[PDB]
Image 1 (cartoon, rainbow, N blue to C red):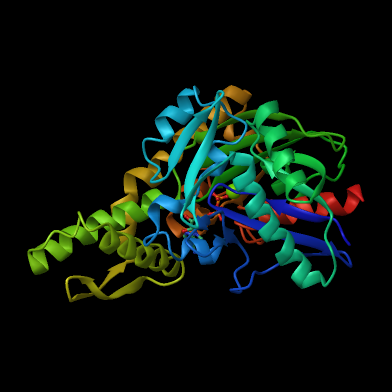
Image 2 (tube, rainbow, N blue to C red):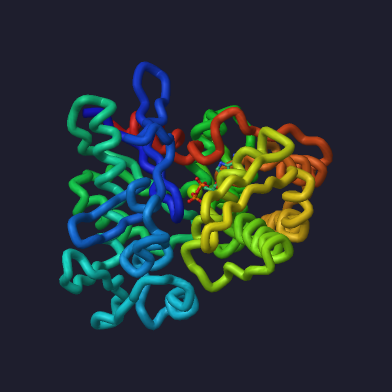
Length: 378
Ligand SMILES: Nc1ncnc2c1ncn2[C@@H]1O[C@H](COP(=O)(O)OP(=O)(O)O)[C@@H](O)[C@H]1O
Ligand SMILES: [Mg+2]
């Protein structure tokens, strides 16, 4: 079986495979090229991926996500302490290590973060196998550039327990560069800027590549900024609209909100190609059908400050790396949020018209690069 490339992401994961000089990003059962990093436990089963995320509104306490934020970390970790204040599931201490606690088939069960991730990993593995029509064993898994050795270890472990022989763990930005071929030797130093705006995390990385060797000269971003924050803004906006229109506040009804959010995220994706999208929700609150729409202009207006602030981490990355806009040779877009027009304009304007690398789907770039790296490693 060919070695595969796996992007084990915070909110979305992707698997690609190099074959006949071409990289193929493998779609899942539902036909999507990326699958949510969600795991849900019920009375009768364990749901992973889309099936899992498609019921989080119904089974909040038993639907686990954000496992990547826990992996390789300690319970006493300030990150963990701050984080768990927002997850609808339990995180318990176990001799220092944190564990997620769920109820599976009536009985209480706990899992180490690496076990949750191995579940997502097994899902990607069978997606690959379903496509290849053969067993996948070897793999290259990606990790953020800021991951310490514990976090890398845990990611490796998640692989082993998922039945995957992890050939190598490579940084996500480096995987993005390899996807565009920016790793080929041109007898000169090259500075690449990776602008990664995903589902819930934002990362900016400046790589220096000479002789084919990478050198992460600097990094920046925000671990709590992503496409989900843009969704929230739409939600708050629509909650206020429903109120004016029906003098009812649906805030308390978690289900109404969760369904509205799902409609928003979808409208958001449509907004990246169309100037407006309709929000059609049957029986949102009580028996009131919420039928409305948003325009790209209003969308951009709701997230203006968020979008604009995206440039601060870019300026920081520059000054830390000791470079000026003029010195960065290539800029590659990574993450599903970079498909947003305003974000592309804004970044280009900042780099005074410089062309942006974006021919490869941004949310598939890391997988793409890992698959290539897997191919050379085997
Ligand atoms: N067309 C699009 N326009 C805007 N956002 C998009 C689009 N397609 C996907 N996204 C967003 O990308 C995010 C997922 O990004 P992705 O990079 O796949 O995840 P991760 O951050 O987990 O690595 C979600 O917030 C999703 O709404
Ligand atoms: Mg990502």
